Length: 122
Image (cartoon, rainbow, N blue to C red; front, side, top):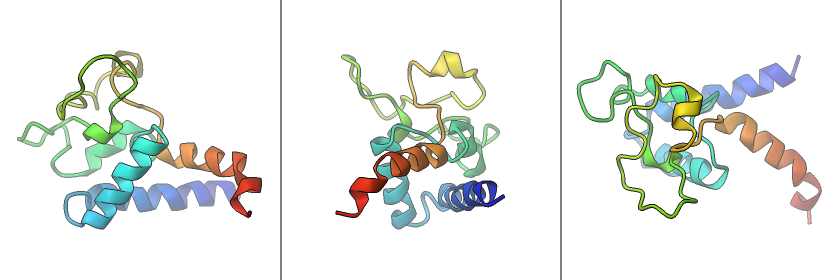
C-alpha cells in the first residue's frame, strides 16, 4: 500500500510525541511547532490528545479532555489565552472548529510537502 504504511509511520511517531509531550522538550517543541505552523492538532485529528495521560477525558486536572493551546486558532480579533483548547476532545468538530484546529497534522504536513516539493530542492 505504501501510502497507508507511510501515514501510519507519521501517526505512530506523533502518537509517541503526544505521550512524551511533557516528558521531553524536544517532542514538545516539534509538536508545538508543527501545530502552529501547519494549523493542525494531533496526528489523525485533535482527539489523539486523549492519549496523553493529562489529556485523557477521565484525568483529574484541568487539561483533561482538552487540547494544548498550540492547537487554538489565533487569526481572530479576540485575546486567546492558555485555556482555549479546554473541553474540546468530546465535542463535535463544528462546535470546536471556531476555537481550535481540528484537522490532523499528519495529512496537513503531507500536502504541504507535495505542494512545495519542487521548491524544496533549490
